[PDB]
Length: 29
Image (tube, rainbow, N blue to C red; front, side, top):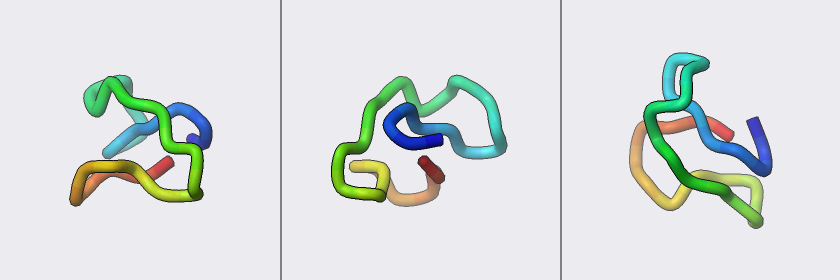
């Protein structure tokens, strides 16, 4: 959910991607 990041559609990643991709491996903006 760019900018916000979400794995299964929930606030679990706790991060904000600014390049169209979460900093982690498994989450989806």
